[PDB]
Length: 190
Length: 294
Length: 49
Ligand SMILES: *[C@@H]1O[C@H](CO)[C@@H](O[C@@H]2O[C@H](CO)[C@@H](O)[C@H](O)[C@H]2NC(C)=O)[C@H](O)[C@H]1NC(C)=O
Ligand SMILES: *[C@@H]1O[C@H](CO)[C@@H](O)[C@H](O)[C@H]1NC(C)=O
Image 1 (cartoon, rainbow over the protein chains, first blue to last red):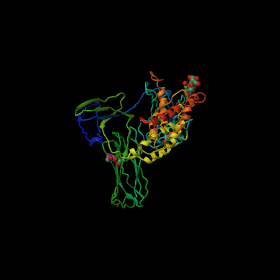
Image 2 (cartoon, rainbow over the protein chains, first blue to last red):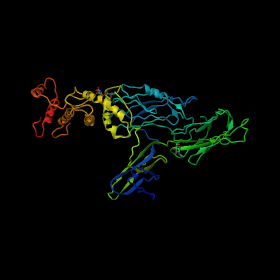
Image 3 (tube, helix red, strand yellow):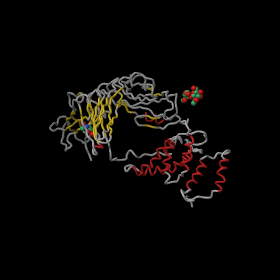
Image 4 (cartoon, rainbow over the protein chains, first blue to last red):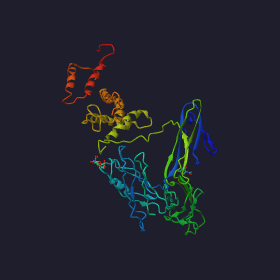
């Protein structure tokens, strides 16, 4: 029994045949409250998940994703398409946890990379997996760094017409206690 | 095989909140005949379609006639959405050009139906919860409260539930892969042999998976252990390259992970019960009598 | 494989392998493996054949 605040109660049932049956049900309430009740013999476990978006406009935070997009503006008829975006990043909390794993680097709405493939192809800094996702970039496994490094890479304009809101590609995990340290900047050519 | 008409499009992408992208449509006549095609799109209140070519109809072209046909649209909903357009050729209008046959077969009107994704506003995540209930011929009930709305975005948040017991593993496409002797180093070799070992367990266990590549991975493992003969220590410990570091211990995940399977691997090629007791007896030594040894 | 061998020499030495375990290093693995090979040959009741 899946009962909610809004006078709502959906029932389900399970057996040897419903064993393998996924029973998906959602609700639209801003109230999130989930009373349940079952019966029978043995133990069994159900699970929940609550999807939602975040980061409308976060405020600044400890970590430094150093990204720079282009010469400060398109301001020319040829631009909005070819602009190499240079990204330059290292957090300091780097101690005795693991090898260098984390990154995320993706495209904005309507922008296709090529040479970005080839610049990642080049980079290798004393040790590297030459790892790649074909929408992202993975040259990270190495020893603890106080430095950063950087790179630069452009796109081609896949979208001629684009409503105003940016794309931002951030993942930021350094230490359990502190805030999780985001740093950001979008594309200005708009 | 042939069609004289085919539709190319603007694949939108998983796109931004503001949904006014650039949707176009283009059909091209590869038949030599100039034919009128009456066209429109099937829309809904699920989005805010906008007529770019409001007053005038994209009308008529000839063999390989290039025309770009687009509209503006700024949806309301989020998630994957299909877009249905239709393009039909009508008769009795020999006026767009000199003439218009417009007499196709059962593939009369060209219609295209396109699932495009819209990405919502903001960075995406979820929150879940985990609840069991185990009545033993009885009854148990639980309550779960589902709320963390700080710094919230418009109409963004939803949720669901399920439970499962699945049987019948279909398949194995998750299974296969391979790597080798690590060209860069003998350092990443620890992450080589470590999962390499329990591939023994899968050859036959799986009934979907590819045992042969795991029956190859033993072909490798018939060398894998030989490195561990080299990566061990004389006193008995193990390192990335082994001994020359005496009065110390080392990591034990890998030796603990393996030393069983060294004993499952002690069938095909022979490792002794000396290699396992020496591993062991090295362990017994590190134990203090009272303290959780430093 | 499934056999034993003479033991005068190994018994004669395995001590001095442990007196010789000062100058150049032989492990306490080399002596317990020698040993544990011996414990196996013992029956539970019979003076093993
Ligand atoms: C990054 O900073 C660390 C800080 O520990 C440097 O490591 C040592 O720094 C001390 C001074 O704090 C020096 O006396 C040592 O010679 C440094 N080396 C070591 C490993 O002890 C480190 O050199 C800096 N560079 C990187 C990339 O780690
Ligand atoms: C949209 O198209 C996809 C792929 O053809 C299909 O799986 C899905 O059911 C369609 N959704 C509809 C019919 O709205």
